[PDB]
Image 1: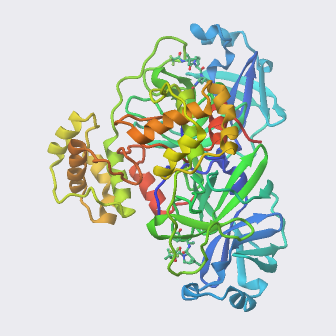
Image 2: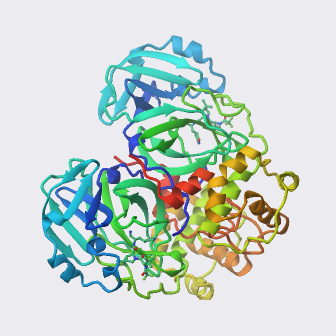
Length: 306
Length: 306
Ligand SMILES: *C(=N)[C@H](C[C@@H]1CCNC1=O)NC(=O)[C@@H]1[C@@H]2[C@H](CN1C(=O)[C@@H](NC(=O)C(F)(F)F)C(C)(C)C)C2(C)C
Ligand SMILES: *C(=N)[C@H](C[C@@H]1CCNC1=O)NC(=O)[C@@H]1[C@@H]2[C@H](CN1C(=O)[C@@H](NC(=O)C(F)(F)F)C(C)(C)C)C2(C)C
């Protein structure tokens, strides 16, 4: 009953959050086993960030220059290295709350939960999508850098995002946990803009299935369409092409509701060409594209985590 | 940068979730110190729930009939009692993860986070409002009963909601942690309907302030209004009357933005009488009323929890 944007329970990630200070710059770090991961611009003054030479700034630092605080306990730093745009601080204490984890690089269209943190302390959790233009539509203030995005599978936390910056129009950019940015962005205070974004078609279809599962059914028309003809229409309205892989991923929802993916594509085609005429779907006046097919299954089938 | 529905970090509550089974009925319980709290209808068969006599059903149970599982560990039950619609199971082990906590009864219009659980295990977290008709618009499946709603203040978890049932139109109903239902509902499978709902006016105003803080400003008109005249208009569109207490609670946002509450009331009055003309506010095509003034401050000022 009901369908909501829903984040993963954050407790496993909360126990990994620490504060990292270098000089007068403080941000969040992620403490897994005996390594703390954080954005490399913790080593920058405000003036360094206009055109930093990270390798140069880092050669002038030593272990003791990094103040790492887990709550009210300082963690002694015994090694450091730079991996792409991420700094790795080796500490002399393994985090006893470390969950089973992986580092993954997610694909555009996939969703994850963000645990927004300041000074190493969690402020809130929300659900995000990696946009096709490799930005995310988050909520972040000064000092949020080093907040992470993650998915959970039973007992395993898959970390996929570390926050670094905000761009014009207010969208956010960051890296995977190997320090590689999503998209063409750089961690420098210089002129940068996101490319034009597009609508994640497979996710809109997943969300229409969620609507049907939840009894919100007015938009279902009596028609079908071809994959080729749907994608012709989708292009006009700035929607990602639907691939056969996407059709296959939608199969569980298609089987659950008895609606073929291409039949649902016919209904979405009408909605795009005609609008929603002041009606809502699942309480929303716009078509929603930040639920994956898995998100829909997970929420409508009550999948839990251990 | 950005404004999102954002839940409290759930870790403190995750460490209190347990599974409670009686007979063949299983649901979630909340384990604080040496007491487990859960909905009393765990003692009902499917047929009992049509017209249960809870006192009668409970007199036929003894301590050993209650199977309480915290992960893979069974907690021995050494006492039980019924308090309104909640069952309290005394166990022989205090929960070592118990946070500092309070039980509170929230008022209509206030928000909280729900940790949706199945079989004692957390599935996800989302933000909810107590509606003026004493329902909540949640996302709950079979077996979710005993999931709780809560707010966090620094280190203190204020539990305010325990989930019990879903009503026609798909809205949900439940109790505070003393077992008293919000609204006129009863924990019986019988014909029940929510009253007509209304829009939480103070929260819409808080959300308009969030829009201004985030630079989304088109709806601001050049006018002002009286409290009396605004509420005349608000009545027509099924909005709660705005009280002076509400004006005072909005003062921090009014001071932050330089916009008097009654000036913002003039802008909201235009939006109601005129619509949004296909425009969005903070990405939304409808006026949003599930952010409190505190929610707005907390998200735009980065308040954290310890
Ligand atoms: C980390 N704590 C912050 C998070 C930012 C701050 C406000 N909202 C956020 O998401 N990260 C930064 O301040 C980064 C950081 C230098 C500058 N920066 C920016 O986000 C800047 N953005 C850009 O220069 C642009 F447009 F290219 F993205 C700023 C103008 C301050 C918003 C570094 C090392 C990139
Ligand atoms: C607890 N696990 C469930 C949560 C429900 C189940 C589906 N979505 C939810 O939120 N609670 C119940 O099944 C409760 C419970 C008996 C019956 N019940 C209902 O929710 C029923 N609702 C009503 O009878 C109504 F309309 F009055 F609210 C049901 C028809 C099964 C949806 C008790 C003890 C009230």
